[PDB]
Image (cartoon, rainbow over all chains, first blue to last red; front, side, top):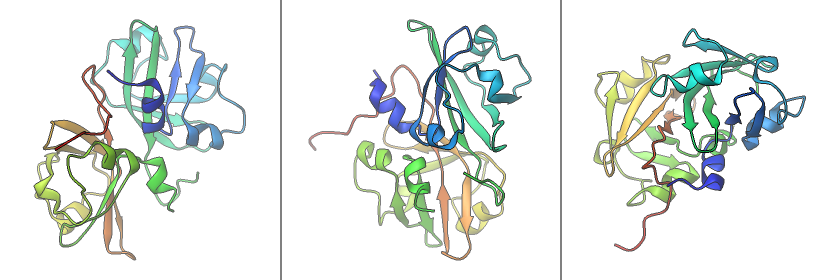
Amino acid sequence: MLSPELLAKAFPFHFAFSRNREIVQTGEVLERISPEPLVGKLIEQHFQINRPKILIDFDAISKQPRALFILEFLHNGMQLKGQMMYQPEEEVIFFLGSPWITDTTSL
Amino acid sequence: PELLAKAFPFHFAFSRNREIVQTGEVLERISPEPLVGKLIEQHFQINRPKILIDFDAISKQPRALFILEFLHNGMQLKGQMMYQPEEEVIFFLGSPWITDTTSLAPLGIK
């Protein structure tokens, strides 16, 4: 029921990836923040998954739809937390992440 | 900053009297009634942690993930409660859990 334009705007720090681990879309704020452009790049060159303890693996990720995911943006060290929303029809996962705001979190 | 208002379109901010003083762009769009000036407990419940809706109590859980439920439709918003001592407000930087059913459409007439 969710508009793709609405989803993207609702989550300014999201990224979406395909099963080859390539990033296919990013939110407005995330893109503006990254030094390299993220679309076309592999997840593991820009992110680390801190929680749950699992592989950056499309299939492994699709098996945990209720888990709170915590990813680190390797560039600034921000801890992004959120849902990994699986779209089986599109063969895309959306990490609908947003940063924890601590005193030393720099955007 | 006031980028915070933009990067968290579902946020709301509140004061010690539990009055909502500010809301994100998307939260207002989907709300059945304007939230600014309303009391938190008329519109939301806290599911996690198992705490009172209380400015002081919330301010002492700075590292907890809060789960609030928007009472109107059962939407679960998850996020940080970020205290701002200099402004005398807490920001709930929540985001909705997204399901097949999720609508981020404005409500229409009535």
